[PDB]
Amino acid sequence: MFIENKPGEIELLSFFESEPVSFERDNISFLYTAKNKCGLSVDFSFSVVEGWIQYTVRLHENEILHNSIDGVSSFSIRNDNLGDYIYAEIITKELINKIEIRIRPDIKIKSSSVI
Amino acid sequence: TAQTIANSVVDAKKFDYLFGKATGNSHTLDRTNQLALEMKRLGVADDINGHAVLAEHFTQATKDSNNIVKKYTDQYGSFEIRESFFIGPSGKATVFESTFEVMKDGSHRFITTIPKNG
Image 1 (tube, rainbow over the protein chains, first blue to last red):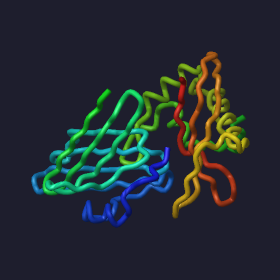
Image 2 (image 1 turned 90 degrees about the horizontal axis):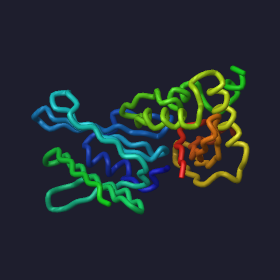
Image 3 (image 1 turned 180 degrees about the horizontal axis):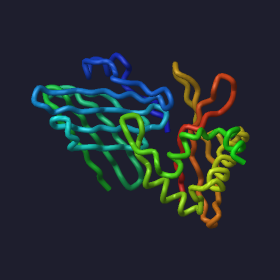
């Protein structure tokens, strides 16, 4: 499944204040990284042609959270009074999954799965 | 036989993914459990017969032009999703939703696939 609606490469550049760490041609997939000044880091990646998003959170380079979401056809960068966040929503007949990733001012992930 | 696999659309590296051995990383979504369980359900063993059965099916799935359900093109290239019906040696069946890149020389490159039972 293809991610047909994604932030532009410039929008992601602003959000992560860095170009992608790496690009995989096989499945058009990108990895981005962000850190705070306390040893907390987050790896955000997605594949345009296979339709997924992944994120891993590391504290002092030890993995503490990993999430993988299949069946993404779009994700977006949104803003509220607290700052910018990556937003992704997966809607099925029975289930609604949401993820919300903030890296500024703080690294903060909010996710949910409703029936 | 082992040349049937060589002329197929399924790269040798992709057979680790098909049998649930493509462990995940930043650029690879881990579907090892799902794919391993499905191959066992369909009766496709991680042997030479198993590889040839899959190789032939995904190669043949590119030969019909009436099973393409979605196309996508960006600056990197042209890609397509194909639906294909597969019944395995166990008698259980699934529909494979497979993603290919349509190469510049016209050939098809297997990228990934998902079984959809229901």
